[PDB]
Amino acid sequence: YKGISLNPIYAGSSAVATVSENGKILATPVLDEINIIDLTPGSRKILHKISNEDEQEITALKLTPDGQYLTYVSQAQLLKIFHLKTGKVVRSMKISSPSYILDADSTSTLLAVGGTDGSIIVVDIENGYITHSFKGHGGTISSLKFYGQLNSKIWLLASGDTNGMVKVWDLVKRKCLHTLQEHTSAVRGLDIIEVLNLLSGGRDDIINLWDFNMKKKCKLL
Amino acid sequence: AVGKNKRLSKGKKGQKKRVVDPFTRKEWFDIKAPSTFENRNVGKTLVNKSTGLKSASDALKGRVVEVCLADLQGSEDHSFRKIKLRVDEVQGKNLLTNFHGMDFTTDKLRSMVRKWQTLIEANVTVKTSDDYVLRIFAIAFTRKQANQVKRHSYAQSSHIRAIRKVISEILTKEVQGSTLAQLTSKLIPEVINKEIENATKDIFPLQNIHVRKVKLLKQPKFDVGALMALHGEEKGKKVT
Amino acid sequence: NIAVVIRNEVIQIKLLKQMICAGFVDHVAVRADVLFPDDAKITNRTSIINIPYIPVLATRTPNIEDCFVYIHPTSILNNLGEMPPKYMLYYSLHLGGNNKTRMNTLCDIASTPLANIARKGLLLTYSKPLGLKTVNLSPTERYCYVVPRFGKIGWDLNPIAVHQKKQKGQWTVIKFI
Amino acid sequence: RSKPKELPFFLQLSGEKVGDEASVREGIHRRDQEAQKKLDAEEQMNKFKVTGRLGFESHFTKQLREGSQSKDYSSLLATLINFSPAAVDLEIRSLNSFEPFDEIVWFIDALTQGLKSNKNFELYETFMSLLFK
Amino acid sequence: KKRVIDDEDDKEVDTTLPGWGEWAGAGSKFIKKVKGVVNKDKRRDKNLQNVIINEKV
Amino acid sequence: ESKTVVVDDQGKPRFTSAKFESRKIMVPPHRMTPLRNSWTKIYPPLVEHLKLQVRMNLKTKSVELRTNPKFTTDPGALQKGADFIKAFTLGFDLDDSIALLRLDDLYIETFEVKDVKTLTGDHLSRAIGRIAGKDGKTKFAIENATRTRIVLADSKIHILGGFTHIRMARESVVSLILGSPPGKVYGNLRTVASRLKER
Amino acid sequence: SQVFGVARIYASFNDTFVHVTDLSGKETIARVTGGMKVKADRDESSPYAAMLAAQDVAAKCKEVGITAVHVKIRATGGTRTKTPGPGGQAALRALARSGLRIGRIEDVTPVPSDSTRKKGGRRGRRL
């Protein structure tokens, strides 16, 4: 008898799915592979399985806002960055900590990755070399957020801890520009909006809005 | 087995979907020990949730942690003792704990018990001045003199009974004159057993004299003021 | 590069001159006996001339291939003597007074460095393998001692052990030994 | 037919060799010898280290060359016949095969000239067969 | 002669055990004498230019 | 690290690039004399091949193994070392315990005659006699047959070897404890030995 | 700087549990099991099984954010045997390898002062 098999798409692993700016592209981890599917009205189909190893499950995965690069960290403590055009794993590098938080810039250029140890590293996407590594606070990282215009000179990285702490760091200066201990629990979410204002969602119950400046002006709005 | 041939039992009829995310719904609390020990901050524990402060407070009023005095005090030579603390008053992520019991480690007990000597186990039930009914087990082993030639060092039943009586009266006098915080303060630097030795030094030369175990049995009416003093008030931040 | 902006900062002379050769090929020359060595230590005082007698070669230039040259006076090696190395690699030749040609600037080099650089280049047309063994690992791959030709003609150099391969009908060289 | 006739501290054993039938039931050096052969080759390669100064172009191939120049191979045939068998095989094997095929063409011409000469018939045929080999 | 002098001489061994004192490890960080057959100073071949006597035998 | 952002085409940014652990294991006295006796053959494998600082607190009769943050390489080296010393303490020969270091799949299993069947006094002595066999012939037969090492303590018996091997050795030993005479046991041993050799 | 759990390693005679909990043993974090990682039942108490079990639990513990563990190994105790087996040894080795910081090892095997009868019967249990 002829047979056709329907396979599940988002299964197993506890990592968030991701999409580009257009619904056309979706990434999703099954327990060991990473389905990519083209979402087109009516003609929703698949691009390609990737099957590095069936044993270690994908820990977290990000898809750059333009459907060009996919970056995924596995249980083995190493990141694989994968080109979508050529459909090929371009680079790989260990990260010395089981990471769980990925964030790609609006521009397709930078990707910050943060893991349980507390140190986070931000890497150039196109060229597999990290820019700089942040020792950071001591708790397990909870979220990351980038801020930078398409053509600007200011770039900010906000990192949220499992403790009620959020550190805003400069990228062109790499200083603990402001250390904000305000939540009592983990900072699940983060967001930067232009004038500056900062958003921090403390998992306990709270959503904090900080009026903020490149200079020491940083108060609870 | 998760094998294909492991045939299905009544068993796997209706499962439940893993959607709860338990260690996202849960929460972290840190505990603190009384002021007798030196390192008071030890470890963290988990509470199911906080939606019921009923649940939070009740779980942490039932909790009982169990640490080793080496970890607690910094000196690695208390490796074999191991105390039990129970937390009963909680405030602001931070748990206040007091003494709840003692024991050795099974390795140390097997290590002390050797073959050519007598073991003596004394067992006294008492109550402190704090109204904490308590039970203390002590042990000792009949060592041998510096010019022994006899292979063994056995004591007679008479010497055994005399030493048991002495140990019982020493333990009860000490822990009836004491209070429970004072009891732990005595029990830390091995002073009761120094007394036991120094008292039994004329009946029979002993060795490895230890206060093997302490057991709480009854507790008095609770006292949050006593706890806070034993550990040695706050405002908020104007959310609007 | 780390630390984005750019700042300027035994010294292994062998590699230094190997590098300089990689730059300055092909304008090479070899000193020739015997008017250059201490035979010409006679007889002036406080200023001695050691008559430079050096055939310049470059196969890309068969005309000035194998031509006698005299040193430039401005060089710090102006008619100096008792200097060890044999091949001198120069920047540019120029004709001046007494209808005499001289080299611009120099580097002192020897056999196996010239061999390395020209190998990476083009000029070393090797010989048949050479009593000394010549082991073949596979029909394509063999080791062999070869004397190369650095050359209307050019000289040769010392024999070198070489790990060369057959491909495309020639015994191209992989690495030296 | 005339070639003559002729540990680690941390062991790494397997699930059947030691008692790990579990890993067996869920069951999950030639390159080393190649590396060692490379190494031996290096060993003789740098053990023979004579730096005597030897001519670039061998006598045989040179003589062939001016034979081609003069379009007559008499001397080349003379020396080819005077060779020793091991030699003859060595050079014929170690000719060249580049694009222009000049060496092979010249050798073929030499053999044809010899067969015209009507001398050493057997050795000229056998040289031709060796070249074809 | 040097060989036999050192053979016949009184040995002195080092009986230290790395350990018992303190950490005798990769990172960082008890002597007795045994009488030989003859001490070097007593041998009846000293001040003999070309002689080698074996007190051992 | 000097530092400036460079703005590339499309204006996008570009930058440039930029635990000691301890364990303690005690030693009984009757196994404390031989530890001193063969100590000099013990620390070299610990320090040279495992890079593991050692010590012996003879004022607490323990051996302390601590691993350095930088010198050691293998994380599991510490645990293998602890196991090796532990086996030597339980009473195995030095070279046997070294084998326990060398490999990675050697285990030690212990149990007791009262764990198998409650025996009292003279019966228990006879049972240990039946395990040992005259001049240890029986125990040596089992060890050679199943490629393991057996040590009888007073009543505890310990078996070192690979997993299935110690299972087989335990099996035979338990039969001996219940009371099958050494003749029948030896017959069974030679049968399983032939089968294991063929496989 | 770190946080500590307590890894309770129950090495039964024909299975193995590796149960990680918080201090005070109340809030269980991860629990795996021999056969559960090995789909058979000869091998449900095998060193390989326990090795996989401990590897996975180390994964889950590193999830939750606990970096060190004290360990309480255990045998079935009671009237049965009383010493942890190869299963427990394998689990311990695998986990320490996996790189959680091991703090303090104990053997909390329940040893009856005065046991009741044991399952065997007068003739003896096994074989």
Image: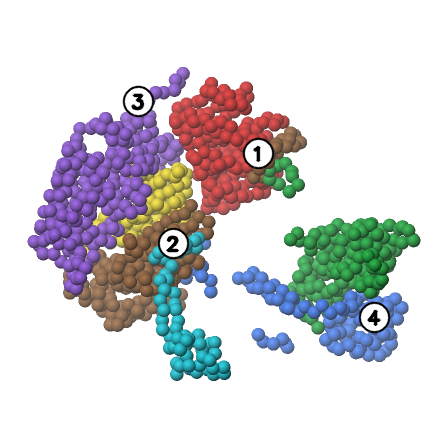
At label 2, which amino acid type do we have? Answer: Trp
Q: Colour of chain C?
A: green
Q: Colour of chain E?
A: cyan
User: Image check: F143 left or right of C105?
Assistant: left
Circle 2: element type:
loop
Let me know if residue F26 appears in the view.
Answer: no
Mark 2: few, some, or many residues within 10 Å (few <14, many ≥20)?
many
Q: Residue at x 83, y 70 (%)?
A: D63
Chain corresponding to yellow in the figure: G
Chain corresponding to brown in the figure: F
The residue where tag 4 is placed is D63
User: Image check: G65 left or right of D36?
Assistant: left
The residue where tag 2 is placed is E23
Percent coordinates x, y for residue G125 in the rendering: 21, 58
The mark lying in front, picked from 3 and 2, is 2
The picture quadrant where one finds residue F17 is top right
Cα separation between marks 3 and 2: 50 Å
Q: Residue at x 61, y 63 (%)?
A: D38
Cα separation between marks 4 and 3: 110 Å
At label 1, which amino acid type do we have? Answer: Leu
Chain corresponding to blue in the figure: D
Q: Colour of chain B?
A: purple
Q: Nearer the viewer, residue F5 or F13?
A: F5
Chain corresponding to red in the figure: A
The residue where tag 1 is placed is A110
Which label is found at residue B233?
3
At label 4, which amino acid type do we have? Answer: Gln
The picture quadrant where one finds residue D46 is bottom right
Cα separation between marks 2 and 4: 78 Å
The mark lying in front, picked from 1 and 3, is 3
The mark lying in front, picked from 1 and 2, is 2
